[PDB]
Image (cartoon, rainbow over the protein chains, first blue to last red):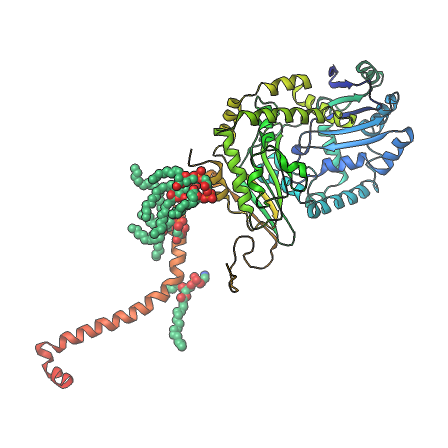
Length: 431
Length: 93
């Protein structure tokens, strides 16, 4: 279904869907937050809000277009959505407002107003959004002094020094033809999209992006943002995971599905077939947890995030969850693998097969900037079905058994023990 | 079981100190460090600093009580010698 062409440097990829009632086109760059330095951190956040500025978005509304933009560790995207048949105007808007003319957007009183608003967006994120600011400090401590440790939103201290001249430097170095993929999702044909691009000039810059000296490397460490005025405790814990282009990519994803997510206030969440639940329910140890498996270009992270009000029994929560991770190496059963297979296929079919062409454009553009193509959903189901119990035990013994960990936390975390007591739980002396 | 009185120490989660806000801590895993870092440097320069700050509080009392002891030992030996018989009768009697 995915069709990918090449044209003088830029790559065109589409995912046609006749039943859609909305087409979407845009450009996805293969550079993100991991391509900055601790002094220009936050440049890609300013470029996102300049694109969605009031004057820029007022022009788009008259033609009937809506704008979106996303910033990640590896990629950033700029999307224009419109009704089918209006795809010609969306390409025209992208050309003369972001690709070829950035002077009007980068004017004074428009850069000074956007910078004022972003400085407020990160001030309240740093003091109101606790679960998402300990997952950001987990990246900061696990990849310290490496490119994979800078926050995607930037830093408050770093954003007060950025000027308009720093935004032109980043655009000249990264917004290039060799670093870009042109995407189209929804009700739009591959032949029509490529014909429109060649009917115009539609050429980005010519240079190549700079290369990074050092790669990302995991380091076992911890950071503690203790605050005794907050009513809860938020904790994130992870080991080194898998990159995107790995043979164990789906095996690590299936492993996180065995433990899954949990909500204490949902009656149906308390009946899940997870052996961890019967340990943490007699005494209410947590309100919620989720197990993740994040992959990037260089490395990844595998672990869980928790939030609890039972501040006197945090040690019990950590001890029981890590003891269930040990069974992935020694005694994982066949019923647990079959259940996690069915729930992973449903979860994948709800992310790639949603009804939002904007979500599809980000997913499709990011997978082509890394491996030059997109793996279909039918082929991934065949790879998930092939996983066996011996595969899980081999992967867990290599990545989980007796390995270093990274910890982040905030709130009332006096009851969280030291690093060595927690690291002792990654293995059993009885085995 | 009945409750107990009021103490000045608690347990994990309710230790009983002031509320803490604004302090951040960082640490690295012991498996990624060098346990014997700087032992030769500390054995000479740090050892000299520690000795130089406390050696006056210990040696002066020690030297006072050692000079007292030696002076009392020599006097007793002289008293029970042939040259101290004129003093032994005039003191111990």
